[PDB]
Length: 49
Length: 49
Figure 1 (cartoon, rainbow over the protein chains, first blue to last red):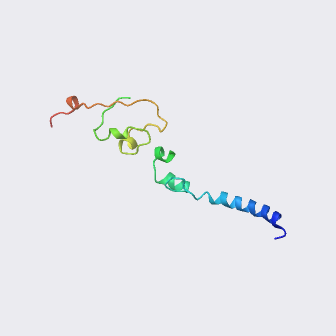
Figure 2 (figure 1 turned 180 degrees about the horizontal axis):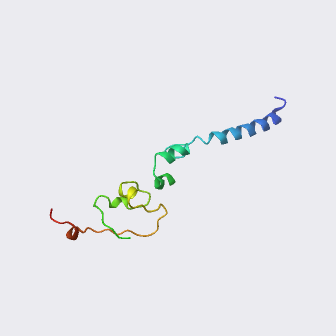
Figure 3 (figure 1 turned 45 degrees about the vertical axis):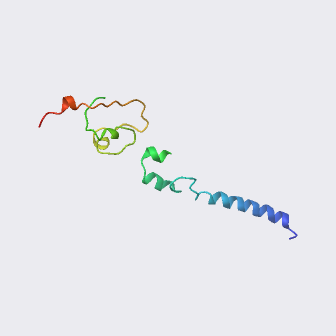
């Protein structure tokens, strides 16, 4: 671990991007994560909220 | 806008509600602003027979 610092910079950036991309799958309370399904099986008034 | 409908269909006169009269013969937008007023008038529209 002589090059710990440079390696740490690279890994921190990669991990940040990965978690940002992964967070698209979370539902955050909505019935589903993909926008299409929400817009398919629900009326516009409820699809808004 | 004035007209006459059945009893259990008054719920269809509202934004974004899909039904049978809100689908084929009277539709109001999802960005509506106004009021609806419905009162029972079985006294004057119901003929015997």
